[PDB]
Length: 330
Image (cartoon, rainbow, N blue to C red; front, side):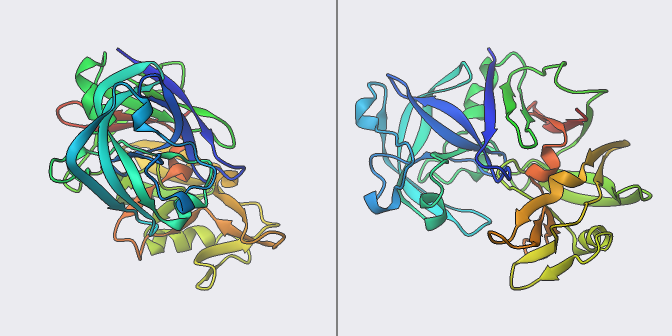
């Protein structure tokens, strides 16, 4: 089997991407944030504290003839941005772009933190990291991809995120029309539960490529590109007036600037992020200070190849017995 679904930016900055997902019988369609950095499929629901729902579409398990309470199971997750959610668990039928999994754990939120409430466009998350990170207790549950894998034509999914435009998540096949050149595959460590890999270096604009190993994670659920402070300083030093602002929370730059590109290495291959992809707009409405899309990871503990990086590539998440990642230009 295969599936193919369009993913759409939630706003004009590509702050996140939403993909429609069918849950239950009859189908209830919710727009979920597909997140290769986590492993829980959770949704706003009829159980979510009413004051914490503000415009999201909710899953109502009592209206699904295939929903079954997973007795005793609870979940609770905290994300790198400080947000969190928790609740109980149902199993139900879940379909993405024509690909159906029966018995998928659907984690129903009883509580969500303010940033989720405040974003009316995201009805939940669909985790695509390794199932070892799934938070359901006392019986850990499998991701949608893990449950689908054996049925897929090939045990892979691909992320093709757009810049200020829709893109595609495919399951079970590699669309050879969706990229240019060849796909370069690189090794993955699953030891932390992530799609963790080692970039071979970087360049700023037209500058020379610096060969240096950068371990980090391919994370569709993180907006920006988070890299070591040395790399980030070298980038922003090429932008007149750019500075790191403790009060804003990262590098800002004059909105009048033209940003240089940023290149990252995948083996001997190179992925070029155009400068425009690094502009996240005014820090507050009407400001002439703009927020940068490349930020330091120094306070995170891990480097994160988020959407800013991934949207410049066609990315293969290869879930073969030994997982690997593939990157192609497009």
